[PDB]
Image (cartoon, coloured by chain):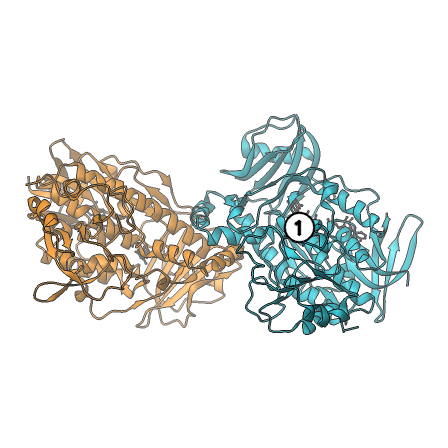
Chain colours: A orange, B cyan
Amino acid sequence: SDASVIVVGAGPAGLMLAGELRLGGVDVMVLEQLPQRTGESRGLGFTARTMEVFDQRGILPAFGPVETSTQGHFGGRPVDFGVLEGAHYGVKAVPQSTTESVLEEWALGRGAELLRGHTVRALTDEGDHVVVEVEGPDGPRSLTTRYVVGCDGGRSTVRKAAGFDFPGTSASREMFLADIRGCEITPRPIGETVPLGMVMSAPLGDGVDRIIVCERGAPARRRTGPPPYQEVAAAWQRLTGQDISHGEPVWVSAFGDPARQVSAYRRGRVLLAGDSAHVHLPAGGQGMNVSVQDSVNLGWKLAAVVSGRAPAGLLDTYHEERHPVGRRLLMNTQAQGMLFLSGDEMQPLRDVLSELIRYDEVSRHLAGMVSGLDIRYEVDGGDHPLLGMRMPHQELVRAHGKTSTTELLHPARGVLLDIADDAEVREAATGWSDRVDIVTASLHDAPPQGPLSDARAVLVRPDGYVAWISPGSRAGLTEALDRWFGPAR
Amino acid sequence: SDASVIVVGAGPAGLMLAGELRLGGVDVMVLEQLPQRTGESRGLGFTARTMEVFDQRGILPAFGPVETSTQGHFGGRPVDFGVLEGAHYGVKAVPQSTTESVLEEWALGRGAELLRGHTVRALTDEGDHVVVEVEGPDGPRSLTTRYVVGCDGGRSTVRKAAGFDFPGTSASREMFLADIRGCEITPRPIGETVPLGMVMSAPLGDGVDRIIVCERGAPARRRTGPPPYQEVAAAWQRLTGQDISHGEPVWVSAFGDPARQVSAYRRGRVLLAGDSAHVHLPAGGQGMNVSVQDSVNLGWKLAAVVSGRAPAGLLDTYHEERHPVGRRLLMNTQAQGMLFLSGDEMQPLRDVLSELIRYDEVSRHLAGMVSGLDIRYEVDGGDHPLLGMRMPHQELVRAHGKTSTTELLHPARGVLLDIADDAEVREAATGWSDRVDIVTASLHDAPPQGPLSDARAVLVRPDGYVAWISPGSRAGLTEALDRWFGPAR
Ligand SMILES: Cc1cc2nc3c(=O)[nH]c(=O)nc-3n(C[C@H](O)[C@H](O)[C@H](O)COP(=O)(O)OP(=O)(O)OC[C@H]3O[C@@H](n4cnc5c(N)ncnc54)[C@H](O)[C@@H]3O)c2cc1C
Ligand SMILES: Cc1cc2nc3c(=O)[nH]c(=O)nc-3n(C[C@H](O)[C@H](O)[C@H](O)COP(=O)(O)OP(=O)(O)OC[C@H]3O[C@@H](n4cnc5c(N)ncnc54)[C@H](O)[C@@H]3O)c2cc1C
């Protein structure tokens, strides 16, 4: 068995997972077909929760000094993300290429094995293990592993190989994206409706503008490689009345509006994460974020099962917790795109949306949805609001020195947070001290009526979601720890 | 001068106005080109506020015993209208033909002059008066009046004649509506998306179903008379896979999605009200309601100016108060229609809408918008919530006998409501007792913390909107009465 887990594809999803797996104490092998990273940088910046999952692991400093704004939109419509206590829009500029850069450097630091110029062509789940056919630099090889995770993007080889179900609709439009030099092109962050469809445009920073075009009737086409630049340019004139012949392209590509999502996130011993599981219209910046977050859901869980520390039942929760999120990803993103991408025909409906956004409830809700902060998993049929949601960053007073909720998650074991000083709780948990870090501290600069007010103790999973809280969970701590970390030692 | 005011067109708008004008103590002449009423009954039922404006005048009993539900939609999406204190969806079934029937019988009762088989062909505003060319039963006549009000529907002759501005967009789709017999056709109140577009269908009551069809690519066409039935039928099969050859039609018509609204509601001495001022996609049942309400805004005001009781400045408020409402009518209705009328392509966006509707703020807001109960006019830059909104029905204790806010508006003079017993207020107003009914009473079954709690007095315009409230208006009662009823006597 050449490695415990084989990850195929080394994009955000795969890189994040490879790291998460290593921290989980597991050897891992990433096969990526590309020899050197794309150079395309599709998305710009990342969401609040993606910011937080990076921070959970001490990855943010590698990004260089960065900014975070509260001014963002839901499908063009400005939403102030402040209205939801402790939320914001994200980190502003960062190109995917740099995120991907970062995460590679990380996981390699975490001792993951990355094999480039390695293309997976077929695979078979034999029951106790999985075999994988690979065309690499020196030729075709055959590898054996305990789990394979398809992180190979929108047209996943893995998903087709392992026989997944991929229901949904194929694309109906073709849109263009170009990053151009030289031309003197107006900003259109919200975009702009022109009789023949819509356009958008923004500046990025050193001589380069992004254009997006949507010629209304354009059919969907499968193509070999990007469109030739002059074809996009031709499209831009027929829409704006601007000639961009003279433009020198950096990247040019076509893309579309599909909506498909695997009906099961796991089959036997093969799993999918990122684009490979859910493919959609790129809109409201979600693709990378939600994918990276799939990896953070799965990583620790898989680590546990691989090493015999958890019953395979823990791994099903990856499906149960994420299919829903990916489904909402299709919903969120297609909605957002339809507002963004339509005629003067969609104007009435964004006029009402603008009217509704004005409330607090509404403004929170979409700021919740976009940022990924509204995620609540099923964990316990109890009263408390925080149950099953993410654990917010809160500074803590440890014996000698201050520390943070966020920093205790650096190692990716569970965190049990004794705040009231109850030896009774640190005892019930002793049988798990190998898997959960029992920490006893007090709160520092809490907002006197916040989510941790009147909380004696909290159980935080390795992905930083809350699994159990005192008071106000149906189940005792014993039931809870067994659920997520395995039997008592 | 043959009559004070000439109203052209005797639909909901014109009939309502003719009545409102008579109560205002003014002779009025309605010219309608049709000799006998259409027989078509496009809309079904009416909104809360339309219910209330009818009731303001004692018109509801003529309707026969009727029902009112709280279960309605915003563009297909179920909204419980209850969530907004004292709101609901409307009266359920009533066909326009019966409403039109009712209102005719009313205004004739009110002593309005209705001239049928009379078609207005041209008109000239001469400054001090207006002339009107009319082809009637015995021939062409020329009439003279002080005001003309275009209530002649979507293709208003008046509006074109008097030279109005009618900006907006002409229709882009063609939809079909048919009322059929015999066929066994499924209900589709929310409608239903079929690959080739959308359909809807409901039952109405004695053997007759309504179908609506939207064949996606259908262009807009100007036509002489309705479409032939077999053309709609052909459309229905190409969409549903159902043959309705055998169907016997009662009414068949085509209709579309325009969006236009006169930029000024008044020019010199000519005015517009109803369809003639604002034309749109029929969706969310608004056309009749908002139009009838234009007439109720204008009627009393015009009555005042015609008879020299108010300075012409009162009449401008008809524009200032209603252009905004009509504008929101275009917005409301086109939004609602776009959700209702689109592919599986609009599904994500009604999925978020369904999510937002779940709140209270949102559910109220749309229930407000649809019912027409959210209307607040500019009247005074003051704190109080009720200022400029409609006066809600509240039972009152008069000297001998109980009565209601609603019943005091039967005569269509203003109502000043002394509740605290303050002779100081009944004095300031003495100079207007000719135009305002000074009433002193106490509240009956008020909801102990309602909108009239801690209110000494209220000034209610003839259209039943609140103009001044103690406490909490910038202006004193004197300023207020002069604003709406004219100088002190
Ligand atoms: C126009 C554009 C703009 C976007 N903007 C945003 C944004 O603003 N915010 C956001 O969050 N998302 C955005 N996205 C979406 C985002 O780019 C994707 O979600 C994300 O980059 C893909 O995640 P992934 O790691 O699962 O797959 P990918 O990034 O596609 O990586 C999959 C990898 O698998 C490798 N691979 C595939 N098949 C094999 C195989 N047979 N063997 C070995 N390796 C294989 C590929 O080489 C590839 O490197 C945008 C997308 C587009 C197209
Ligand atoms: C498919 C359909 C369904 C609808 N459903 C609803 C609904 O559910 N709820 C709702 O509120 N609204 C609905 N409406 C809209 C509603 O029907 C219109 O708003 C309303 O009936 C028109 O109001 P009106 O009185 O201003 O004009 P009209 O009702 O059009 O009447 C204008 C009158 O003027 C007369 N006229 C025109 N020109 C002249 C002239 N030259 N000389 C003399 N007379 C003239 C005409 O004969 C006509 O009788 C619907 C409309 C359609 C088409």
Q: Is residue A205 visible?
A: yes
The residue that mark 1 highlights is: B52
Q: Secondary structure at mark 1?
A: helix
| Horizontal side, residue B366 vs residue B420: left or right | left
**Quarter occupied by residue B419:** bottom right
Above or below residue B226? Residue B445 is below
Q: Position of residue B62 (x, y in %)?
A: 75, 42
Pointer 1 chain: B
Which residue is farthest front?
Answer: B400
Q: How many numbered marks are there?
A: 1
Q: Position of residue B282 (x, y in %)?
A: 62, 48
Q: Position of residue A188 (x, y in %)?
A: 43, 66
Which amino acid type corresponds to the residue marked 1 in the rendered image?
Answer: Glu
Near-viewer residue (A52 or A185): A52
Callout 1 crowding tier (Cα within 10 Å): few <14, some 14–19, many ≥20: many
Residue under the point 49% across and 50% down: B363
Q: In the rendered view of the protein, which quadrant contains the N terminus of chain B?
A: bottom right
